[PDB]
Structures are given as structure tokens and as C-alpha cells.
Image (cartoon, rainbow, N blue to C red; front, side, top):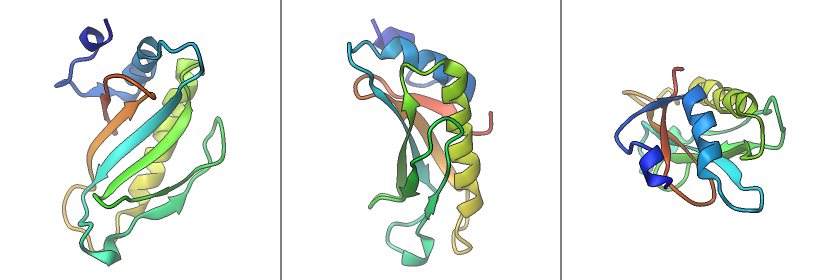
Length: 129
């Protein structure tokens, strides 16, 4: 079972997650791996809008933007990808995100970061790993 391979309370490192999202993807087609991050901003305030692009080391087409709840979502590869390639794409997105903490936001910028495939449990990850 998948549920028992993921600890909902545990925070995983970028490497661990990459190797775990492969055991969660069971579909016969190739699921997309997606990164989500709840930002330390206020959706209410407009000068706290995060919108930038980034080139994935292993891919390339990706531009992010905060949603109505101050959250950022982005695909970082396919579940078929070798684990080390997912791990690099995950870091490249974060390291890029962190450079955009708006001047008008006080507090931790990365409040929660997790990874998911098209179906299944989410994998909470330590972004500083």
C-alpha cells in the first residue's frame, strides 16, 4: 500500500522524496511530478506577488506564479525520470523561488513545500536539503 510508505507527519529531504515518488506512481501511463509551495505572503496584498520563470536542468518549459492562496505549483519532470534527475529539478525550482521573496513580506518565505504525482499521498519536503 502507498499510504503506509508515506508518513504524513514526517518531512523528507529532496533526495528521499525523489526516490519515494517513484514507488507512489503506479499508473501504466507516465505521471507528472509536481512541486507545491505555500509562500509566506498574503494573497490579500498585491505587492507580494511572486511570478518568475526558471529553466529546469532536466526539462525546460516552466514559469511559476502564486495562486489565490499564496501557493506555488510547478511540474518538475516525470515519475519515469531517474531519481537523481527529479532531485535536481526540485532544488532548481526552490533555489529560484527563494530569490523572489518580495521586499514587502515579513516572516519565513517557504512555509510548506511538498511533491505529488497525479494521484496519491503528498510528500512533504525540507527545502533546505
